[PDB]
Image (cartoon, rainbow, N blue to C red):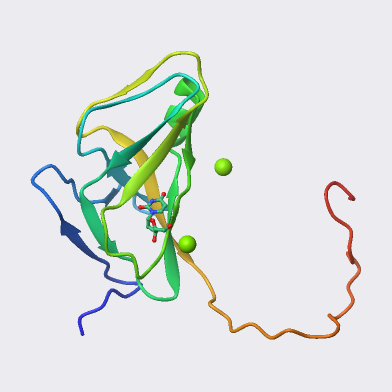
Length: 144
Ligand SMILES: O=c1ccn([C@H]2C[C@H](O)[C@@H](CO)O2)c(=O)[nH]1
Ligand SMILES: [Mg+2]
Ligand SMILES: [Mg+2]
């Protein structure tokens, strides 16, 4: 019965190591996500980081795991995967890619990504015989 809304999102800690998501500025797009454990993201490699949080993203939205800009510029860290469905009730994981040539060390509590509650539509699909014509048309992949 009790469901998240755009104004109030429900979060459950799955262990004593989880840190609640928190926005770092007044109008920050995302909630900072902290690692629940120590990890090493190998050079040119990847690592799935557990937050030990379960989140109920409000219906009409999804949660996008997104990169922190400092770790991207300084450490060549990117976020893979990243689509968290509003019906997902498992452990929120952050998939990190390390494109650099040095390992990237993560300690428990380090903020290693952010979580953006992005508004979406979930339309029904109708197969049609023709689509409306536009100026763009089939122009894609570097037309403009
Ligand atoms: O970065 C990601 C991508 C996916 N998932 C989970 C939630 C999502 O609903 C499910 C299937 O993509 O896996 C995560 O925890 N993190
Ligand atoms: Mg990308
Ligand atoms: Mg899927």
